[PDB]
Length: 100
Length: 80
Image (tube, rainbow over all chains, first blue to last red; front, top):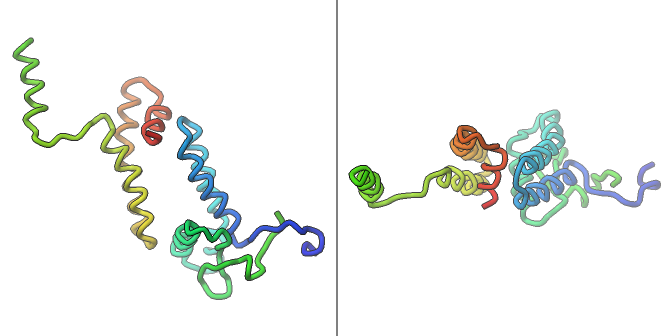
């Protein structure tokens, strides 16, 4: 249904949350005062999604979250949790998407 | 007073190698070690991150004891 109703999509599987979290971690580098701690806390809280997606699936969430953080920093903004074989991959090319 | 002042300066000079205090070492290690953690990608990445964060207890405690708001004094250090 959503494939017909919403033409504007973003990669799922935590991929969207990863890009936002990264951009927040970089943004906070220029912020001083109480706001810096709260922005970073927001960037951390967003990871609850790829975290619980891994844990509920029986995956090693610590390994996958580490791979997502490091792999994402390479410029591939669609990395996310793969549920076919425990790994990370391009969830956009794999058609794992959610409406923007 | 001169005898006291000479003792204070001497103690500083006696140490052939000195490093700035006031939170400089802890704040600098906080940022540097946080970057180090990103080169691991296993388990020690978390231990390193928590180790680095632990060092901030010093500039935080110093700010509180000074009667200043640690959320600005420590945050400004992280920025600089």
